[PDB]
Amino acid sequence: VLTVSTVNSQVTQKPLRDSVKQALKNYFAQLQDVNDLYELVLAEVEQPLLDMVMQYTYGNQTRAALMMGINRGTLRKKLKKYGMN
Amino acid sequence: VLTVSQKPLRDSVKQALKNYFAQDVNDLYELVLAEVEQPLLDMVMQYTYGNQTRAALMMGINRGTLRKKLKKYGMN
């Protein structure tokens, strides 16, 4: 269960989606028109995911793709997309 | 651009994967994706007050994809 630790005014522990809700919330007030919010968020999440995965598997695509649950082709598509290849 | 009150959202994702990895995986992608789509759909839908037309435009996806996803997370 993906969770994130944090420190409040005085330390705490909420799921990942919360951080997402906050960023989205914060983002809206930041406006004054959006048109590619999806791809925008995906990228802000796929890359860190890729890093963590690739880091674990010492860049071993195969062993990495097997972890995320996707085929090598796709993985390569994303890496190349985020220029990590 | 997507940050939380002041670092990027990606940092949270990275830490969440850090604590998680600190424990095997088989469908990590979907795991993370759902953890990101639900709140997204939810936030956008609430933002456009249920106006799926504005929502899809805002997200950059067709009405179908939006209905598909919303339905996927029982947000229908």
Image: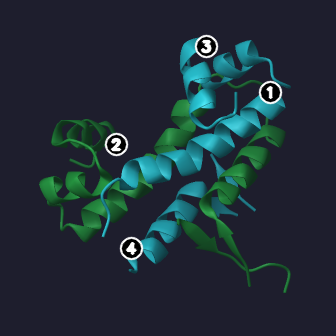
Chain colours: A green, B cyan
Asked which secondary structure carries label 4, the reply is helix
Identify the amino acid type marked 1: Gln
User: Which of the labelled discs sits on residue A82, or is there none?
Assistant: 2
> Is A62 situated left or right of A25 in this image?
left
**Answer yes or no: do the residues labelled 2 and 3 have beta carbons within 8 Å?**
no
Identify the amino acid type marked 4: Phe
* Chain under disc 1: A
Identify the amino acid type marked 2: Tyr
**Answer yes or no: do the residues labelled 3 and 4 have beta carbons within 8 Å?**
no
The span from disc 4 to disc 1 (Cα, nearest Å) is 38 Å
The span from disc 3 to disc 4 (Cα, nearest Å) is 36 Å
At x 75% / y 39%, what residue is drawn?
Answer: B43
Question: Which sits in the foreground, B71 or B61?
Answer: B71
The residue singled out by tag 3 in the image is B63
Where is residue A53 drawn, in percent x and y? 31, 61
The residue singled out by tag 4 in the image is B21
